[PDB]
Every structure is written in C-alpha cells, then in structure tokens.
Amino acid sequence: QYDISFADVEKAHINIRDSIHLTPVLTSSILNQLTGRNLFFKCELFQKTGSFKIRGALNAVRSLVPDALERKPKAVVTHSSGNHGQALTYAAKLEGIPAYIVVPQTAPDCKKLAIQAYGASIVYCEPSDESRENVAKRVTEETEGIMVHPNQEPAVIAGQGTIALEVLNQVPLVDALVVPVGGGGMLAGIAITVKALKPSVKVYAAEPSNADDCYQSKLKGKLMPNLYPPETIADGVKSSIGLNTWPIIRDLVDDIFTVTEDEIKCATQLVWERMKLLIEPTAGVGVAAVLSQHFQTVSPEVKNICIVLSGGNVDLTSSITWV
Amino acid sequence: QYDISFADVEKAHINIRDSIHLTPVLTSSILNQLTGRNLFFKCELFQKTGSFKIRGALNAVRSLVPDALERKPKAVVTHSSGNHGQALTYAAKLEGIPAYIVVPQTAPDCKKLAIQAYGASIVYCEPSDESRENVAKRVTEETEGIMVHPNQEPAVIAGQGTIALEVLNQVPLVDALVVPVGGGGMLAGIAITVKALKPSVKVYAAEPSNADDCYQSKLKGKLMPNLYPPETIADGVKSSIGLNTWPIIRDLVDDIFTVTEDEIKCATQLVWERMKLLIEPTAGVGVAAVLSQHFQTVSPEVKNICIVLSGGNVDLTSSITWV
Ligand SMILES: O=C(O)Cc1ccc(-c2ccccc2)cc1
Ligand SMILES: *Cc1c(COP(=O)(O)O)cnc(C)c1O
Ligand SMILES: *Cc1c(COP(=O)(O)O)cnc(C)c1O
Ligand SMILES: [Ca+2]
Ligand SMILES: [Ca+2]
Ligand SMILES: [Ca+2]
Ligand SMILES: [Mg+2]
Ligand code: NA
Ligand code: NA
Ligand code: NA
C-alpha cells in the first residue's frame, strides 16, 4: 500500500538497535499544569548525533544497496548539511565507509567548517539544482555510494518510525503522539507504526505557520509543497512533504496544528527554562502545538500525549540572537 | 554521632517523597569516553524548583515548628532569592502558607519582579545586616513562621541525604558519588546515607579552587572557612562549610577535588553541548572534578561514578559572559 509497512519499521529497529540510544521519556508538572494535558517528552535530543535522524540514516546505510551488482554501499552521499548530514556521516563512520556532502559554493564558511568537523568530505556544486543533482548523482556513481534523501527515502522513513515503537513501549497508556513535520519522514514512519499497532492512538503533526505546506496539503487533499523557501526559526522543518510521505500523512495522520514564530520561540524558551532541556527551536514546534489555541479542540479523552523532542543541535554561541 | 543520623534521612524520605520528583539518572557515551569511567548523572536539575534544595526545604517546612502555640508553621521567611529561597517558597506553596522574602528597599526593580514571579511576598528592610536580621526576626515572629538555614539546619541536611537513597537504588553497582560542596548540607546528607547503607561506596566532594575551604579543612583536620567571600562562577557553592556539616565531612567523605574556574566553565559548556542539559555552573563543578587531572589517578576499581547535577537555575539572558 504505502512506501513502507510496519514490517519495514521493525526491520529498521532490528537493524539499528545496537547503535542508537533508547532515549528516555521525561515529564514536567509545569507543562502538565499549563496545557491541560498529561505530557510525556520523548527525548530524541539525547539521541546519538543530537537528533532522531541517526535512526533513518543508519537504517539506510545498513539496508540500501548501491547497485544490482553490489550488495554493500561503499560511501554515502547527501545534499543535506544539517541534522541529516551529521547523522548520515556518523552512520557511515560506524560502517567504515566515507561520507560526502554536496554543498553549494555559496554555503556559509561556518557550515563548511561544521561539515568537516563532523568528519564528512565536501563536494562543491553550483547554487543551482541542475548542478546539485549533477554533482550528487555523479559522486554517488563514482564512489559506488548510496544517495540518502533526508525524508523521502523509504529506508529513512522506516528508521524514523522506530521512535513510535519505543514510545508505545515506554508510555503504555499514551493517547496521542505529537510530531514536528518538515519532509514528513518522521511523521510518516511514526504514523505507519502507530496505526499498525494501536490505531486508537492519535497521530498529530505540528508545523510552523510560516512553512505550512503539510497543513495546506491536508486541507486541500493533495500535495501542495511550499512555493518558496520558508523563513522560520524552525530550521529543521523547512523541507516540504514529498511524494513518498504525503500519502501516509494524508491517510494516517489525525490532524495538523500550525504555530506562529512567536509560539515556537516561547515554547522553546519554556522548555529551556522549565525543563532544562536544550532543544533546538525545531523541537519546540511540537510543544508550541500542544500549547496553541487550536489544540483545545482536541477531545478531553485524549489525555496522555507524548511530544517528540526531535533534536538538540542548537548553536548557543551564534544562533542565539532571538532571545 | 552528628547533627543527623541515617534515621533522619529515612524520615525525610517519608516526609517529602509524595511531593518531589524521583529524578532520572542519565548517561553520556562521550563523557564516559573522556573520563575512562562509567558515569551516571543524577539529574537534580529536573527537580522541582530547578535544584535539589526542595528536598531539605520541604523536610524543614514539614518538621520544624514556630515559636507559637500552633505546632505548624504559618509562614516561611527567608533572605534568599536564589535556589534556597525558591525552594522554600515552593515548599510554602505546597503547605498553603505565605513565603516572605526580606529585601533591602534599594533592590532593583528587575530583582523584585523576578522574586514575585516565583511567588514570594516581599517585605522591605534597610540595606544593613542589622536591619535585614531584625526585619526577618520580626516577620518570623509576627507571622508565627520559621526560618530555615540553607545548609546547617539538621532537617535540611537530612532531606538532602535522600538524593543518595535514590542513587543507590537507581545505580545498584555504583562505586562513588561526586557531590559539589558549598555549605556542605548536600555533601553531609549524602555522606551519612552512603556510609550507612553501602560504606564501600566512595563519597567525593568537588569545589572551586577559588573557594577551597573544604579541601583545606580536610587537609588540616579542622574547620578552616574561606577568609573572605570567594569569587567564583559557581555561585551556589560560595558558602563555607559550617559547624554542623564539618564533622560529617571530616569523618565520612573520602576525598575532595578542586577545580579551576576554567575547568568549571569548560565542564558546564561540555554538558550543555554534548548532553543537552542546561545545568547551572555550580552543577558543572562535579563534572569538572571527574574530568580533572587529579581524578584521572583515582583507582580504576572505582568505575561506576554518579555525579549529582545539582541544579539548572541559570540566567539564560546572561550566559554570554563566559561562553
Ligand atoms: O535567609 C535564609 O533563608 C538563610 C538563613 C536562614 C536561617 C539562618 C539562621 C541563622 C542562625 C540561627 C537560625 C537561623 C541564617 C540564614
Ligand atoms: C529533520 C528534523 C525534523 C523533521 O523531520 P522530517 O522527517 O523532515 O519531517 C524535526 N526536528 C528535527 C530536530 C529534525 O532534525
Ligand atoms: C545549594 C547548592 C549547592 C551546594 O549545596 P550545599 O549544601 O550548600 O553544599 C550545589 N549546587 C547547587 C545548584 C546548589 O543550589
Ligand atoms: Ca547506484
Ligand atoms: Ca512544512
Ligand atoms: Ca568551598
Ligand atoms: Mg512512492
Ligand atoms: Na546501544
Ligand atoms: Na529504500
Ligand atoms: Na512497542
């Protein structure tokens, strides 16, 4: 039916378990006091590499083949330089293969340093997509690598879904999961998993209003990507949903809550100050969603809500400017 | 025998357990790798009020009596706007009694607003130690209230010992606890508990070399308070050890590690960046200790080390200074 099944998610958990952390679920009286609800925080900010993306990245390295004639990937390649590129590089290191990040010439110096810091090799392209694609596909071919998309690659989606296997085990009375959405790999993997195992549990997406393609797509009933690059502090969810994640999200996600920039900022600072968790603002999106006006429409029967705190890769020394 | 015994800790546990968090113990691969040990982090930064001090404060509020006909305090009175005062204020809220803080009339508006935000009631004094004391005495008496010493009060020391009761359950094979020391209520409480329950477990203290009264005292075999108020980023450990905590520390604490300001800063930053925990610098003291050169020479038999992350009440709009 969909591009992954529950079986794929389980195969992913088996593939990655020896190398990832089974992150804790933490609680906060204050947040419980504030939102009306009984909250549980799945702490993917404590995951290896600082975000959940190691799950999909490692599953991809351990399950994808470069070619019909070669079973083992000989390198990994991606155009993502953020949490995905960091995760993929780490996954590549674990498997003893090189990682290449295709970066435009126009990338900030700090981004070029940060990539080299996490142990990947840089391959430069032009700012353009024609060049970007040329280069990545060319690097993939010449290194006998796998190209690993941050959110549309089935093995990546299946890996992200393992979060939900853990949550359902860690929080047996959970009523809903709240998941920040960008490309929807995490949302789709989680939705597949929850709906296979216990479909009475709600799956809710949380999204910046400033980048609201998932909302608009669900509203319209077809895939409606952002027409232009979004401006948002939630830097990890600037991707649009894509052709592999959209059908899952359409069919299996119960609702989508959008949140303003100010809501994202206030929820992030609330988590910092009141929970002492260094989440990145992108991980504040799910917290903002549960605090938002529209979340009050959620039935009072939906009491036990697990929010995925998806990452903690925040640049305290530079990024911080909005505080 | 001392101003408390383990019996007092068991009592405090029963007194307070229904109202405080049984904080988690977290781990970090990177910090294991940096120290060569198996580290366990007791997360008192997640405790109510943002530090462990609610333990001693609540125990004191639930066990001390006013100078009045009624056996229950009708108020709490403090000089502290810091971790101590915030802890006492929350304890008062739990008991449905007012918490008053005595504040010089020349306090900045920012401080006063900050004080009122956590729910304390300000009573003004003149800016002298004479006026501060006299106002606090008057308010305590007129309100049929109590005052609670931050580190020498037996009820506080006993409540602090409940940290170790949890650690010994959460980390059954623990070989040592590392505890930041100021007035030493937390250190003494912990030492009593550990030496009563599992005396083969080491109890190590950690303090800034800029405020090294605990180290000097243990070296000399007598209480040698700091000669002047120390300068340190570790605001919460500026107090010297006192007459009630010293005998316990003398007899029951195995060793004292001192750490420089730079070590404290670097340990605190390492915890933010690599563990995503927003500890205050005072809580970085214990981390700094386990990373320090002197600690590296500790016997390899002392493998499983629990560090108390004592607090997370850090001024976020003020971090820039040392970063
Ligand atoms: O202001 C505070 O909360 C700290 C504090 C509390 C009690 C005492 C005290 C000193 C001597 C005898 C009795 C109490 C000192 C300081
Ligand atoms: C990638 C990422 C997300 C969004 O995941 P998608 O699969 O792209 O929807 C959310 N939070 C963080 C921290 C991320 O790195
Ligand atoms: C009070 C405090 C300490 C020191 O406890 P003492 O009993 O005074 O030695 C350490 N860390 C934090 C965060 C504190 O608030
Ligand atoms: Ca290929
Ligand atoms: Ca979006
Ligand atoms: Ca000291
Ligand atoms: Mg498809
Ligand atoms: Na593991
Ligand atoms: Na695939
Ligand atoms: Na499960």
Image (cartoon, coloured by chain):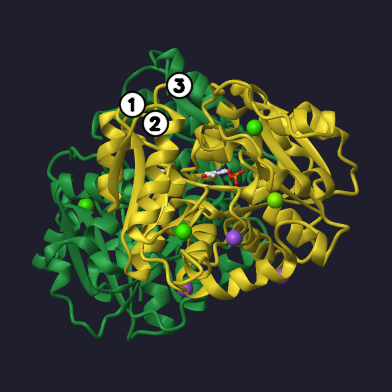
Chain colours: A yellow, B green
Nearer the observer, B302 or B119: B302
Marks 2 and 1 close (CB-CB < 8 Å): yes
- Nearer to us of marks 2 and 3 is 3
Report the residue marked by disc 3. A322
Q: Residue furthest left?
A: B220
Quick check: A112 above or below A72? above
Quick check: A238 above or below B19? above
Residue type at tag 1: Glu
Report the residue marked by disc 2. B133
Q: Residues within 10 Å of mark 3 (few under 14, many from 20)?
A: few
User: CA gap, disc 2 to disc 1?
Assistant: 5 Å
Report the residue marked by disc 1. B130
- Nearer to us of marks 3 and 1 is 3
Q: Is residue B181 left or right of residue A238?
A: left
Nearer the observer, B86 or A208: A208
Q: Residues within 10 Å of mark 2 (few under 14, many from 20)?
A: some
